[PDB]
Amino acid sequence: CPFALKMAACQLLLEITTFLRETFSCNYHRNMSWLHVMILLCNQQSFIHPHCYLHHSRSCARLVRAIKLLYG
Image (tube, rainbow, N blue to C red; front, side, top):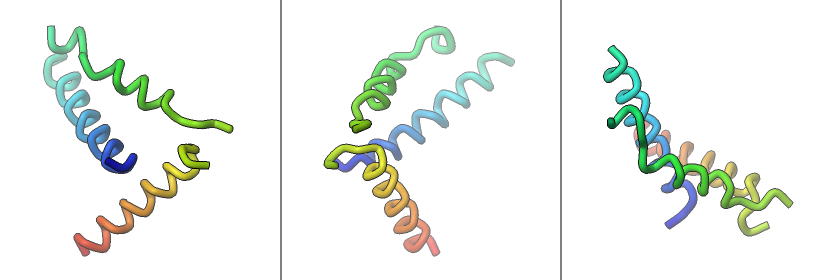
């Protein structure tokens, strides 16, 4: 699967986490399984290309534009 789909999943996880930390603060809210994975996703990049952060950002922007066009 492409990087952009992974970032879409990351956005979903972000919404999950913000909901959990904005509702339980008014255990699940004390430990999170996916955080480590996120760390890996942040470190699994080339900062020197096939897996450079520039290419990933371009792909993400392309997917965002495609989604905007589809939902237009």
